[PDB]
Image (cartoon, rainbow, N blue to C red):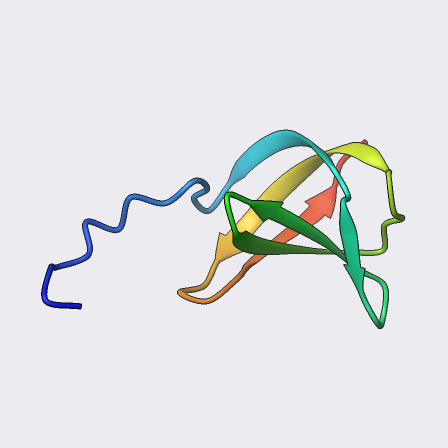
Length: 68
């Protein structure tokens, strides 16, 4: 981009959100796509509504786990 990225992202490392697993990648990774940003929550189900702890975030995708 010609414009610098402000890095204004939805999620940061160490956060928790009440998300619904809308999609799943073939392996068991729940895809929480917030505005298009793909957060992987391994070990979930389609339609599963859980509090995910976003452990860490990468420039292309985020990792989170279910803390019930």
